[PDB]
Amino acid sequence: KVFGRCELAAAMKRHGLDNYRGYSLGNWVCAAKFESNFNTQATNRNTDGSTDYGILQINSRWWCNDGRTPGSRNLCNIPCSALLSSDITASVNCAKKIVSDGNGMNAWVAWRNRCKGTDVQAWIRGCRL
Ligand SMILES: [Cl-]
């Protein structure tokens, strides 16, 4: 599923990501855009053999189990494939744990490099939220 911008915004708000850990909704939509281009089926292979999954490109090195990342962790206790569902509940729940581990949204490189410092509010502008 490829979300619409406001559609995703609505779904994320519904799941309580708006201002979660102080990150206003625009941050999350901004991150989703550059990580996955709003596509839940997005995957990307990393150098070390791990793989990023889903709309927020959550990595199997720590956060989910894909059965091919040896010595890794599964801190969100989920199969990585679950992060590819059209329903973003799993991704959101897992993201909440990630953003809480102490490094905030800097955990997403695309956010840090492309969203941090910019007018993230622009990403939910026009949306009926
Ligand atoms: Cl991540």
Image (cartoon, rainbow, N blue to C red):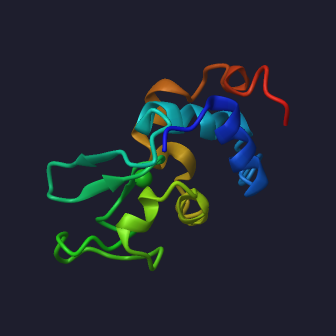
Q: Answer with left or right where residue 88 lies relative to residue 40.
A: right
Q: Residue at position x 61%, y 36% from top?
A: 29
Q: Residue at position x 45%, y 32% from top?
A: 37
Q: Is residue 119 above or below residue 23?
A: above
Residue lying furthest right in this view? 128
Say which of 15 and 24 sits in front. 15
Q: Answer with left or right where residue 58 lies relative to residue 88.
A: left
Q: Residue 89 occupies which quadrant of the picture? A: bottom right
Say which of 84 and 53 sits in front. 84
Q: Is residue 26 above or below residue 63?
A: above
- Residue 61 image point, x, y percent: 29, 65
Say which of 82 and 61 sits in front. 82
Q: Residue at position x 53%, y 59% from top?
A: 91
Q: Is residue 113 above or below residue 76?
A: above
Q: Answer with left or right where residue 90 lies relative to residue 68.
A: right
- Residue 13 image point, x, y percent: 76, 48
Q: Answer with left or right where residue 115 lies relative to residue 36.
A: right
- Residue 113 image point, x, y percent: 44, 28
- Residue 32 image point, x, y percent: 52, 39
Q: Residue 73 occupies which quadrant of the picture? A: bottom left
Q: Quadrant of the C terminus?
A: top right
